[PDB]
Image 1: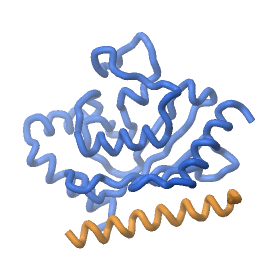
Image 2: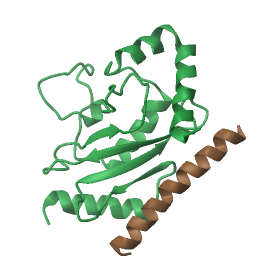
Image 3: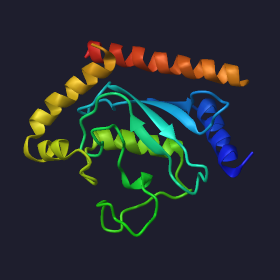
Length: 164
Length: 28
């Protein structure tokens, strides 16, 4: 097995052994460890509380040297999530001379990170709509100019994810 | 565990996550 396969099996074992609260993640099929499905719950007492949000994680051949791609498959409305579902946060951006508008030498991906860490960071991102990427310009603007409406939309996003 | 065991547990954790979230949302 290549380095990538080794690391990914190792990470998954730790996840199955000690399941993280509010986060479920693993390969859709163990014949291909490079494609995972993840489910994360919006943290209690935040505007996305109890939403259940599915995402696909696609890992590069050179993992963990490069980060996975992560895309939500459900409807979302958040400053750091593109209209297509792609999650844009500094920790998922490969170190490189192209800020892609993140931050002052924003914290990039490193092999120190892990799937558990990416997912916990995304959970935090939901709880703390931290406009670092302006991925959804409309959500960015509303978070800034009409917070109370943003909260309204967020509960709708929750209800939709629950199928209610 | 086997892969089959792991895959089944995963599907189960996912169903249960959604069921408990729904309960907490409706309970609130």
